[PDB]
Image: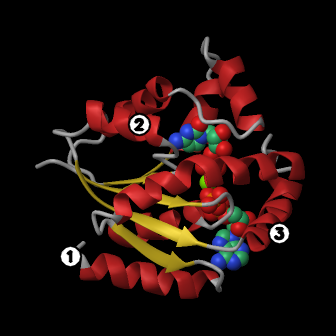
């Protein structure tokens, strides 16, 4: 059987990695964070590394040929699993490249959208910034990540919503309250 795929979207610091860890724990899906895979690719000393580094710091979206390749490598290595793909698609190019490369391999089911205010997301990330040692957890970068979300990614969420394919969870609540709804949703979808 073809894998089920759920895209996990929402702003920087909306809690995507956090909720995805919980789903992995209770449902046994594999968690693919596109941002983390792109970091890993840079730390592994490829030709694209200096490119990826710069784009991450500036909150720009890497060319899809890089990203879709890393997601596909991991997907092909885990036959018989279902996938949470987190922080992807972030723009139209991401999306077109997914449907060009993945369409008859996967059953992409819905977009799980974590809706959260910008001011709350800012505070979360400045707190993760003390200990994360990430290049994009400073105020300069966070604001660049917001704008890219606003200009590029919001259009993608709209696209999936006109096919009734977006499920929205409000994420400005306690972590366990947010997970309660996430778990209820995944159970109701038959997973
Ligand atoms: N519901 C929440 N309330 C408060 N802190 C949270 C909540 N969800 C996540 N966090 C914290 O917010 C920060 C960002 O979480 P993360 O899952 O990495 O976000 P994303 O992947 O969407 O950028 C982390 O420090 C995390 O521990
Ligand atoms: N689909 C994706 C996902 C992440 N990214 C890059 O990785 C950065 C970090 O992503 P996360 O916030 O999701 O960890 C993004 O802000 C962006 O610069 C990307 O270029 N393409
Ligand atoms: Mg993340």
Q: Quadrant of residue 124?
A: bottom right
Q: Is residue 51 above or below residue 116?
A: above
Horizontal side of residue 49 vs 63, given as left or right: right
Q: Residue at x 27, y 31 (%)?
A: 100
Viewer-nearest residue: 170 or 179: 170
According to the picture, the residue beneath numbered tag 3 turns out to be 123
Q: Are marks 1 and 3 in contact (CB under 8 Å)?
A: no
Residues at marks 1 and 3, CA–CA distance in whole angstroms: 35 Å
Viewer-nearest residue: 126 or 160: 160
Residues at marks 1 and 2, CA–CA distance in whole angstroms: 24 Å
Q: Quadrant of residue 166?
A: bottom left
Horizontal side of residue 23 vs 42, given as left or right: left
Which-is-in-front pick, marks 1 and 3? 3
Q: x and y percent of residue 115 in the render? A: 57, 72
Q: Secondary structure at mark 3?
A: helix
Q: Is residue 165 above or below residue 33?
A: below
Q: Residue at x 74, y 68 (%)?
A: 118
Residue 7 can be seen, yes or no: no
Viewer-nearest residue: 60 or 133: 60
Q: Tell which circle, 1 or 3, labels the residue nearer the N-terminal end.
A: 3
Q: Residue at x 79, y 52 (%)?
A: 142
Q: x and y percent of residue 26 in the render? A: 39, 73
Viewer-nearest residue: 73 or 120: 120
Q: Secondary structure at mark 1?
A: loop
Which-is-in-front pick, marks 2 and 3? 3
According to the picture, the residue beneath numbered tag 1 turns out to be 190
Residue 14 can be seen, yes or no: yes
Q: Which mark is residue 71?
A: 2
């Amino acid at each position: 059987s073809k894998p089920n795929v759920v895209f996990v979207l929402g702003g920087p610091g909306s809690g995507k990695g956090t909720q995805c860890a919980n789903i992995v724990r209770d449902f046994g899906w594999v968690h693919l964070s596109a941002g983390d895979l792109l970091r890993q690719e840079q730390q592994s000393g490829s030709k694209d590394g200096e490119m990826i580094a710069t784009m991450i710091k500036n909150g720009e979206i890497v060319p899809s040929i890089v990203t879709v390749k890393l997601l596909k490598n991991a997907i092909d290595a885990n036959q018989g699993k279902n996938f949470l793909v987190d922080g992807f698609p972030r723009n139209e190019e991401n999306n077109n490249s997914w449907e060009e490369n993945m369409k008859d391999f996967v059953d992409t089911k819905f977009v799980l959208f974590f809706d959260c205010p910008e001011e709350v997301m800012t505070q979360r990330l400045l707190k993760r910034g003390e200990s994360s040692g990430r290049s994009d957890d400073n105020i300069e970068s966070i604001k660049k990540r917001f704008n890219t979300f606003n200009v590029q990614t919001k259009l993608v969420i709209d696209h999936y919503n006109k096919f009734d394919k977006v499920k929205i969870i409000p994420a400005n609540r306690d972590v366990n309250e947010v997970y309660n709804d996430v778990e209820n949703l995944f159970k109701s979808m038959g997973f």
